[PDB]
Amino acid sequence: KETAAAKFERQHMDSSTSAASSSNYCNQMMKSRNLTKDRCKPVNTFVHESLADVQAVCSQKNVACKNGQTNCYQSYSTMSITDCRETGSSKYPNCAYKTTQANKHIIVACEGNPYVPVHFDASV
């Protein structure tokens, strides 16, 4: 089993690039981060900022999560992100994704000591 913090890093962190490198970025990343193993994860966002900057969001703007939880936080600044979503021709195990680059605020749920992100809620 993964820790919640480690699962967040695997699913959502990509500090190795400033932005998605091509239209094939999501197909490659969803596969290599093991999000196409048991099924095609339908939707997933990657954040192209340092781990430190993303972890810092847990000390920023406290807001509600979409489900009503009170431990969500919105980044004060916008961040480079890539949205990955399954597209029409996608059929497990042949997963297919649309890559959309953007620059916006991220909202994450935080837990633990240290208090770190454990869920990606949305971007604004």
Image (cartoon, rainbow, N blue to C red):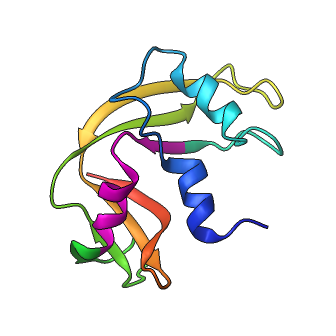
The residue nearer to you, when weighing 25 against 9, is: 9
Q: Which picture quadrant has residue 55? A: bottom left
Q: Is residue 75 above or below residue 23?
A: below
Q: Is residue 83 a member of the stretch shown in magenta?
A: no
The answer, for residue 87, to whether it is visible in the render is: no
The residue nearer to you, when weighing 43 against 60, is: 60
The spot of residue 19 in percent (x, y) is 35, 27
The spot of residue 119 in percent (x, y) is 50, 65
Q: Is residue 10 above or below residue 86?
A: below
Task: Give the magenta range.
Answer: 44-58
Q: Identify which residue is drawn at 48% across, 80% down.
A: 111
The answer, for residue 98, to whether it is visible in the render is: yes
Q: Identify which residue is drawn at 44% across, 72% down.
A: 116
Q: Which picture quadrant has residue 114? A: bottom left
The residue nearer to you, when weighing 75 against 68, is: 75
The spot of residue 35 in percent (x, y) is 70, 42
45 horizontally vs 64: left or right: right
The spot of residue 85 in percent (x, y) is 54, 35
67 horizontally vs 70: left or right: right
The N terminus appears in which quarter of the rendering?
A: bottom right
Q: Is residue 49 a member of the stretch shown in magenta?
A: yes
Q: Identify which residue is drawn at 36% across, 85% down.
A: 70
